[PDB]
Amino acid sequence: HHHHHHTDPMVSKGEELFTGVVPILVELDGDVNGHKFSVSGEGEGDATYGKLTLKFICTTGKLPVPWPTLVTTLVLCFSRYPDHMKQHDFFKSAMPEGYVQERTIFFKDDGNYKTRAEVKFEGDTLVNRIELKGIDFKEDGNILGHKLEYNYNSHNVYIMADKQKNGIKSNFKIRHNIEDGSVQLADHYQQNTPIGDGPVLLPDNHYLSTQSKLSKDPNEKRDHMVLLEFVTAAGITLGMDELYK
């Protein structure tokens, strides 16, 4: 089930790079309130199903923030774009030279993450190399105090063209569950730009529908996170709905 047939050769180029199962490497260097930490992640992506399987390890000891706060930072090129939406897949069109992904994540009544990542192919491996700076976090807040539950919700995040930067932008709110029944809001602002000077596909407005399951490896003694995630593009339906009257 590797065969694909799209009339746009630019779509074909991106679909070819993502056929089958693609190995993934994630590298994060982070700093929060004077504490430096690093994370390494490995696994694979199957864009045909929008399916991601990744295991992350804190390579500096105990992670000083909760694992769920890093899920969005730690490869949207593995989203499943339906056939009628493949012309709007900016993420694959930027490959293999790749794209920069930058975010500010505002934790309400707490600090902010500023992140900058380069997502690109090194040979057959899709690599996500991240720098993270955590600014102005409360020592006893929900983040530095490790008060967030080890779970994750499903989201719909809206993607818009950023014409000025030849890329895309998005903002969306994530809510992290707290033990006492409250939630910690993480307001994400995001922009992506291509690394190379080659052409990219700039999308019409649409959204990505996400779902994620976090778990633990029972044989892993290091601080770690196992992530199973599915991402599907949606939100463009005029011509299609016509076909069914």
Image (spheres, grey):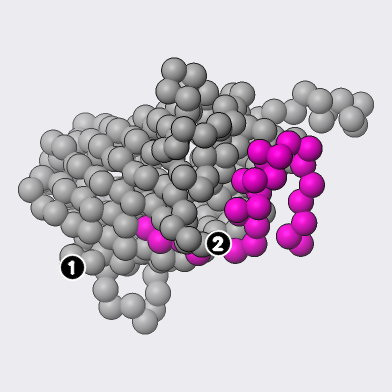
How many numbered circles does the render carry?
A: 2
Residue 18 horizontal side relative to residue 171, left or right: right
Q: Nearer the viewer, residue 162 or 36?
A: 162
Badge 2, how many Cα within 10 Å: few under 14, some, many 20+?
A: some
Rendered image: mark on residue 22: 2
Pick the quarter of the image with the N terminus.
bottom right
Secondary structure under the numbered disc 1 in the rendered image: loop
Front residue of 162 and 228: 162
Q: Which mark is residue 61?
A: 1
* x and y percentages locating residue 176 in the rendered image: 36, 44
What amino acid is found at the position of numbered circle 2 in the picture? Val
User: Is 127 above or below relative to 13?
Assistant: below
Q: Tag 2, which secondary structure?
A: strand
Mark 2 or mark 1: name the one nearer the start of the chain.
2
User: 222 or 15, which lies in front?
Assistant: 15
Which image quadrant is residue 25 in?
bottom left
Q: Name the amino acid, label 1.
A: Gly
* Residue extending farthest top: 164
Task: Check the image and name the residue furthest to the left.
Answer: 34
> Would residue 153 be counted in the magenta stretch?
no
Residue at the image point whose x is 47% and y is 28% from the top:
167
Name the residue: 43% across, 32% down. 193
Instruction: Look at the image and give the residue range highlighted in magenta.
Output: 1-26
With 232 as the anchor, is 70 left or right in this view?
A: left
Q: Do callouts 2 and 1 mark residues in contact (Cβ within 8 Å)?
A: no
Q: Position of residue 127 (x, y in %)?
A: 41, 55
